[PDB]
Amino acid sequence: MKPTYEILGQMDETFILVKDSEYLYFVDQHLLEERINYEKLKDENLACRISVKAGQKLSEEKIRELIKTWRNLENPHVCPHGRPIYYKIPLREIYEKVGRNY
Amino acid sequence: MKPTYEILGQMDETFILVKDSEYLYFVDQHLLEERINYEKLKDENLACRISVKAGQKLSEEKIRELIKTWRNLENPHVCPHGRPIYYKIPLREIYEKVGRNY
Ligand SMILES: [Cl-]
Ligand SMILES: [Cl-]
Ligand SMILES: [Mg+2]
Ligand SMILES: [Mg+2]
Ligand code: NA
Ligand code: NA
Ligand code: NA
Ligand code: NA
Ligand SMILES: [Zn+2]
Ligand SMILES: [Zn+2]
Ligand SMILES: [Zn+2]
Ligand SMILES: [Zn+2]
Ligand SMILES: [Zn+2]
Ligand SMILES: [Zn+2]
Ligand SMILES: [Zn+2]
Ligand SMILES: [Zn+2]
Ligand SMILES: [Zn+2]
Ligand SMILES: [Zn+2]
């Protein structure tokens, strides 16, 4: 994700929505914190059990911290169990559907 | 869109993000207001020229009014020129990508 980005907020207390100029990302808050804790601790089970879970409301500051750290991860793509940390949609798919150039 | 829904906000001063339990919708603010004005005025060119444009910030109240009216339109799907008023993504596509049931 580009270094210029806009955090749109939380959805279903499970995803953080953040976009750059190319994609809208839906970042799984649990998988992201698990990856953060795994890269620090090198222990998959410990990283999992201490991380936030889906269904927890997160503050705006906590969300900023997580997204900032996400960009610096060695593996921002998949959690230690191999699940994708996020879903992304190209912004052009949204714009093109309504007939707009992007 | 179901009558229970959550407005997530504006994106790129062009789309309103709103979801129900099934889809996340990206509603083109211009195409929506144009459809609203067209159903009232029955004049495509007048409805277009008086409607909000992309690139305009909208207040939270204006966004609420538009989304409320959208659900009551005779044609909430396409503007009078035939463009889709919105893009939608099934929430299950987002959840499934990160390995979650939905
Ligand atoms: Cl979880
Ligand atoms: Cl426009
Ligand atoms: Mg252990
Ligand atoms: Mg006319
Ligand atoms: Na940048
Ligand atoms: Na919600
Ligand atoms: Na409902
Ligand atoms: Na923006
Ligand atoms: Zn676990
Ligand atoms: Zn886990
Ligand atoms: Zn901070
Ligand atoms: Zn995992
Ligand atoms: Zn395409
Ligand atoms: Zn026109
Ligand atoms: Zn128009
Ligand atoms: Zn109102
Ligand atoms: Zn139109
Ligand atoms: Zn699918």
Image (cartoon, coloured by chain):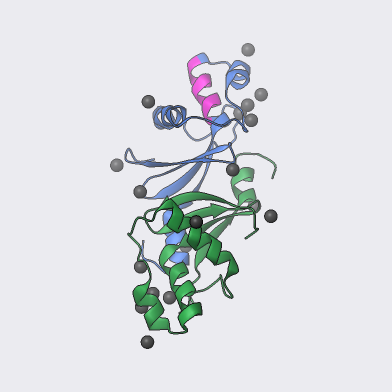
Chain colours: A blue, B green
Q: Nearer the viewer, residue B18 or A30?
A: B18
Count of numbered circles in the view: 0
Image height of A37 relative to B91, above or below: above
Q: Which image quadrant: the C terminus of chain A?
A: bottom left
Residue B80 visible, this orientation: no
Q: Which image quadrant: the N terminus of chain A?
A: top left
What is the x, y in percent for residue B31? 44, 69
Q: Quadrant of residue A66?
A: top left
Q: Quadrant of ligand 17?
A: bottom left
Identify the residue shown where x is 41% and y is 67%: B30
Q: Quadrant of residue B101?
A: top right
* Magenta segment includes A71: no
Residue A60 visible, this orientation: yes
Identify the residue shown where x is 49% and y is 20%: A39
What is the x, y in percent for residue A88? 50, 47
What is the x, y in percent for residue A55? 63, 33
Q: Which residues are magenta?
A: A32-40
What is the x, y in percent for residue B36? 48, 72
Identify the residue shown where x is 35% and y is 63%: B54
